[PDB]
Image 1 (tube, rainbow, N blue to C red):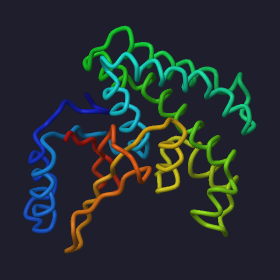
Image 2 (cartoon, helix red, strand yellow):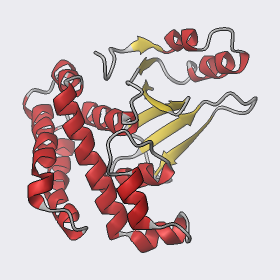
Image 3 (cartoon, rainbow, N blue to C red):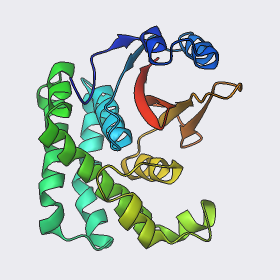
Image 4 (cartoon, rainbow, N blue to C red):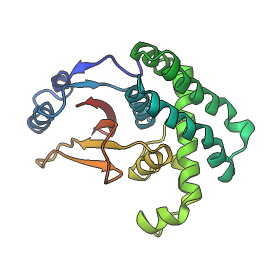
Length: 225
């Protein structure tokens, strides 16, 4: 369990910032709304890895929602092709992602899903897929991302440098894009070391979340309501 941990009590993470007043206050507050946490490896891939694992875990045993998600996943090659990715270069990553969606459907266990996400090869192929899908979604909607995020940004260069490569850290653009690309509602809790309110954001605004993440020290861990 070196990429995604077993479930732990939320206050187990106090030991990560011992004798730190502000972190202790915010983790204690967080423990009022959330009961448990899973830790993810801090390797630069943890947003993709955590969203992928937590969303698929949220589907287990839900036959309608699995059917709908599979229907969307089967269309994602078209998104990739429309953005200029070549099928023979994305095939291995798409196949790995479709494989774990089928495991959610056929096997239906947390244990099986956690084993795939802790398999370095399967897990990294999944992350690479999610990165390419994020890139495709931004590229195909470049006007949207310029209008609403930043009119001055260079979309193609951003995707090439800060989305597609493994180990590249995320910002709110990648979160919004991957949430929209897979129709995943997620809530991010923000814990920094400033003497400020614990606060969160829901991607997109309207929505009931499937996934809750804790963002702290440039890192995403998985929360349980």
